[PDB]
Amino acid sequence: ADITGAGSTFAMPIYTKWAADYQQSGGAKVNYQGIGSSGGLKQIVAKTVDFAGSDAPLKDDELAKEGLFQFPTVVGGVVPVINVPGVKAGELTLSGAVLGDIYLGKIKKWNDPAIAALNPKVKLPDTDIAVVRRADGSGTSFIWTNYLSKVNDEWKSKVGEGTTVNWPTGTGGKGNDGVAAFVQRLPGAIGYVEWAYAKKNNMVYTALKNSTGTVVEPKTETFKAAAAGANWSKSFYQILTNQPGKEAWPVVGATFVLLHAKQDKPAQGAETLKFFDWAFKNGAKAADDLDYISLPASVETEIRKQWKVKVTDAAGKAVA
Ligand SMILES: [K+]
Image (cartoon, rainbow, N blue to C red; front, side, top):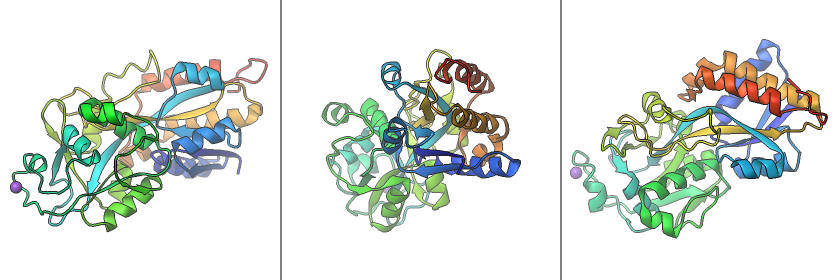
């Protein structure tokens, strides 16, 4: 009840765990509502919460327009999950171009030649594909469609990227949970979820062929390989899709916290920063246990330098 955040369901598993551990350690009570990145952005701007979580980072100009400060907390993977007869987790391989053509509505069956080409070992059925996407404004959708735009020209020009897009086709699930539930129950379903949702629900994720041509499974190692080399020190706005590493999982994103740079309630901002400072210091095993990737120590040091300079009371004095 002490501080309240809302937004990204991508980050909800670790924020919820961090908040429980923090309160057990003696820290304030942290309530986090999983409403989607777009809903979280609306609520921090409406100043109905103390911070928002979003996996669709704002550019410098939008942050200045809104008076918000933004910083990353962890990195996570996004995986295709499917419901295909005779196919178990990790057995099927897809690719960026193929994912784009599936979401374009061009590939309609699971025995399509473009899927078959990537799956010599799998006895594919002729099941119709049932496309599932997010109904709510979503940072997971942003990562997904940012990625599709890089690897499928038709998708880039016809649909593009955003927390919402004009999907050519697809059932709309609310949150990562709603997409997960649709995929597990609709035969032939394909969807996209943050990795923790696939693992918790024992979902059938796919491998992906990355830009190097390596078939990579989704796992801590390949998420981490994607995050390598990001220039955090230049800008916190960093998009980690279709990364060039040979073991890089293709669909990865950081997730972000937004709070007002001028704190109407300085003690609220201080408690928010206190919570994430504690999480950076003490929550690394919790993040790893959920297969998120923790930020490098040097990046967390830079974030601390920035939030003492940039999150202040109305007089310009640091809240931390
Ligand atoms: K085959």
